[PDB]
Amino acid sequence: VGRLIYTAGGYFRQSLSYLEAYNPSDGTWLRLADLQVPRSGLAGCVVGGLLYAVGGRNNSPDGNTDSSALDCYNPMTNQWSPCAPMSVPRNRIGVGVIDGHIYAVGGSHGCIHHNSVERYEPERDEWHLVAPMLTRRIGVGVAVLNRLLYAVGGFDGTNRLNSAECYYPERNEWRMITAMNTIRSGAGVCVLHNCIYAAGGYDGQDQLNSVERYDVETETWTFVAPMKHRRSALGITVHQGRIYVLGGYDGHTFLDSVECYDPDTDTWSEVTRMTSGRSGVGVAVT
Amino acid sequence: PKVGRLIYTAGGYFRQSLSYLEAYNPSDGTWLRLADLQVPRSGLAGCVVGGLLYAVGGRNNSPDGNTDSSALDCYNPMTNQWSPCAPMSVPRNRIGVGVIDGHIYAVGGSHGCIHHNSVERYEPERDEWHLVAPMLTRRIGVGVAVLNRLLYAVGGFDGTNRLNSAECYYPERNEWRMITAMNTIRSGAGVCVLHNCIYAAGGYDGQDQLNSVERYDVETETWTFVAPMKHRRSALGITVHQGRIYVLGGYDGHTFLDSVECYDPDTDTWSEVTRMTSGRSGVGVAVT
Image (cartoon, rainbow over all chains, first blue to last red; front, side, top):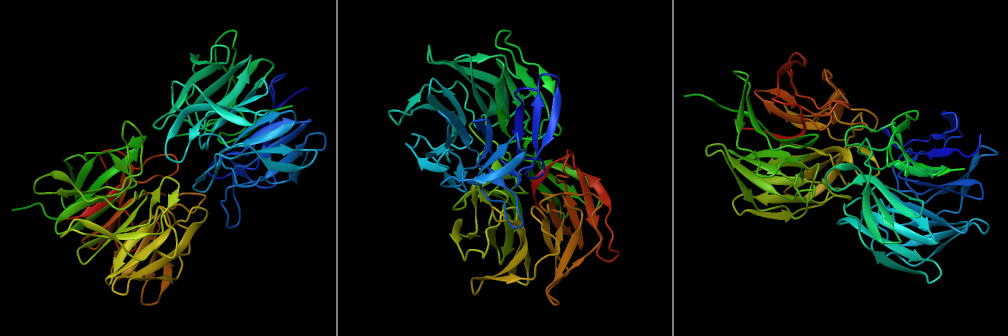
């Protein structure tokens, strides 16, 4: 009954409101307080034991609009409530956390493919812009390592991206790092055991099951064991030293599968089936 | 002496965008395989001018990437040859198309994130495209019909709202004007004109694919439901042949249809009349 893998929002025929927690301990799923507004392409993070759902694209009376919302779920109360919205709608957003600050990265507002980035201070309930990325990125994967922020792949409005860049918070500046072997947008990006993994995504023609991982030591991208299902728009997180991949889109069907990567073994393996196939989820652990 | 008017289906999509050109002969019920598109495309549109067939817009399937297309290709049924013509001013995927006095009107459609409201006219005699009045709405997945030398744009998606509204284009005055709306929100519906009504069949209401079918009477400016199709389908090809509507393929939510349904106006009845060689949707359709 410790930390849970939370899934928020998503899409299946329509944008979803479901909040659901998986407990790898026993194999349980828990249905929790729904999102005040259904949303897809959002990102999930947690700080201070609070779960934040950021950005995406929501559904409404006469609204399928890109979202600049930041909503706070409090597991001890099981309540959602609104926080200060981002400066601009950021659909297909990336998120990272650094010293209890939430970085919203890239995303889109209609045709606008942001390079801008903003930082959220929860105590002050405030968003402030920072240094824009060198590339405009929507569908960008985010991973925090060594108090550095890595933004991986995406779509710049014209080209699908294999490039990745790193943000220095103290220097407040971006520097590009060496690109992946495969173009990926809408991939799942996390950080495990000092390497930044990028799994799945869409290379411009097919959704992928291959996994690339970055070693900052060698500063290079190396393939690993591919996932059993090709997927993009997948939720990702890591839990007690293993990678959990949730849902996604294989090209025809919204997957319910959840796969687990063991770095020691270099093996994937399905561990659950969610509650319904979906894609575009936000994922966090607490 | 034989083989008269045929129903051409061009392009389509089934797990990837296709390049098939197939003619259906309603009289004897047979299918002919003609010269493939030089680039496989789907979500495109088909029209005919001077006995020539035109494939317009869509999204092509190309090794380097799947780009929304701005191409216009003309096929000559007497040489079985496809030949490039002047491309449109912008890519138009999920396009709508009408013909008026031997001119092709490309209506709306998408360019990646762009939801066009603009409209352009192609003059075969010059192989040239020129923009005209933009619609009052952005429309992708829009159905287009020509009635009494006026162009009707029906349903679609404006980027944030699925549309049940339709508008009318007056070529000589060059202007758009909203008309009565449909009973159902429809994107990706089959739109055609039969016996001075504008039929809108199938599509997507934002929740499900549709089998409903409604026609607009320009005289009474009202939208009335008729016999629904027997299959739900969106992104379906449509045409009129010997006073009956033929719908081809489409996506029903799980499967890419190969069924071809025929609507008889006099009995208000649909009926499967044949199947395409393979399931598909997003085809362009024309008759000639």
